[PDB]
Image (cartoon, rainbow, N blue to C red):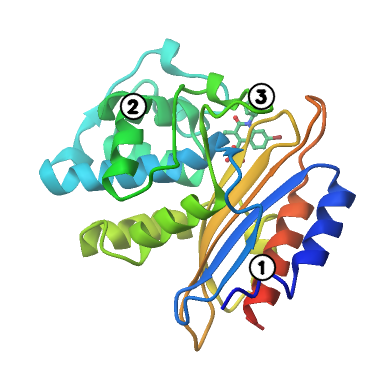
């Protein structure tokens, strides 16, 4: 149930056309069958950390009654670039739950930084990931500095394999209480930024929740998802890219193509 070889040559050709590195890990939750390609290499998380951030908030909500309903007020100086929800509520504030939804479904930067502050910063989110058994994940910096994607720099990285393992634990396993688990799924399902990535490889009659990341440099962008094919167990998968030159462009088409190859490798029609 390493189907990694059905699709190892097509992944290598896709990566050669792209001109960089592609990292994939895909898990069939029914059989436990996996597809790996550069699955243990580090890639920059970019915005993809915001899904784990929302899950860490949900975990804390199990301990702290009322956390999700707490109003948060912020100044103009909190509004960093790409804050499309939080800029509309500057004069009013938003709840923790609303910031978490904005962080997940619009990749809202100001919302992500405000929730990082609630958790004790990048070290607090790293702490939550260690708490679910993820020893690979590290967040080191805040938005926007975490997007530097410097070749060889382990800061603000994880592996495709650790991202998939943690995503399965949070969405399908026992890392969150059932209500919090379904809220995390529902936030991922409502994501607006991923239509050209994993979703572009998934039939319209299958449910999917995803979180994107785009660093803006070094051909670096990513997506992770849970996919619910009809008539079989869910699939969890992560697709990360980087490239050697700062002005290399990312490709959403390459992420969708990689997701297609992972699903073909798992035998999902
Ligand atoms: C938050 C954010 C996103 C959405 P996501 O990261 O989830 O895919 C985004 C998406 C595409 C591009 Br092209 C630039 C982006 N930027 C700007 C880049 C990262 C920092 C400056 C350049 C976003 O901030």
Which type of secondary structure does the marked residue at label 2 adopt?
A: helix
For image coordinates 40% across by 44% down, the residue present is 52
Q: How far across and down, in percent of the image, does residue 17 sit?
A: 89, 51
Q: Which of marks 2 and 3 is nearer the N terminus?
A: 2
Between the residue at mark 3 and the residue at mark 1, the CA separation in whole angstroms equals 27 Å
Seen in the picture, residue 135 relative to 1 is either above or below; the reply is above
Q: Determine which residue is flagged by label 2.
A: 123
Callout 1: few (<14), some (14-19), or many (20+) C-alpha neighbours within 10 Å? many
> Closest to the observer: 223 or 157?
157
First reached walking from the N terminus: tag 1 or tag 2: 2
Residue 144 seen: no
Front residue of 41 and 250: 41
| Tag 1 secondary structure | helix
**Residue 262, labelled with which disc?**
1
156 relative position to 36: left or right:
left
Q: How many labels does the image show?
A: 3
């Amino acid at each position: 149930h390493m189907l990694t070889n059905l699709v190892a040559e097509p992944f290598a050709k896709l990566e050669q056309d792209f001109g960089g590195s592609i990292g994939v890990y895909a898990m069939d939750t029914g059989s436990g069958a996996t597809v790996s390609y550069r699955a243990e290499e580090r890639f920059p998380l970019c915005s993809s950390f915001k899904g784990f951030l929302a899950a860490a908030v949900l975990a804390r909500s199990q301990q702290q009654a009322g956390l999700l309903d707490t109003p948060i007020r912020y100044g103009k100086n909190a509004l960093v670039p790409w804050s499309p929800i939080s800029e509309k509520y500057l004069t009013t504030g938003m709840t923790v739950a609303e910031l978490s939804a904005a962080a997940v479904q619009y990749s809202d930067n100001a919302a992500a930084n405000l929730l990082l502050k609630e958790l004790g910063g990048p070290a607090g989110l790293t702490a939550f990931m260690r708490s679910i058994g993820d020893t690979t994940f590290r967040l080191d910096r805040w938005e926007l500095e975490l997007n530097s994607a410097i070749p060889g720099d382990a800061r603000d990285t994880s592996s495709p394999r650790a991202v998939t393992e943690s995503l399965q634990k949070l969405t399908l396993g026992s890392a969150l209480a059932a209500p919090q688990r379904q809220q995390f799924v529902d936030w991922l399902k409502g994501n607006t930024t991923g239509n050209h990535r994993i979703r572009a490889a998934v039939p319209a009659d299958w449910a999917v929740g995803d979180k994107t990341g785009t660093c803006g440099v070094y051909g670096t962008a990513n997506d992770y998802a849970v996919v619910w094919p009809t008539g079989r167990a869910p699939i969890v998968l992560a697709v990360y890219t980087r490239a050697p030159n700062k002005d290399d462009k990312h490709s959403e088409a390459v992420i969708a193509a990689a997701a297609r190859l992972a699903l073909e490798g798992l035998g999902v029609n």
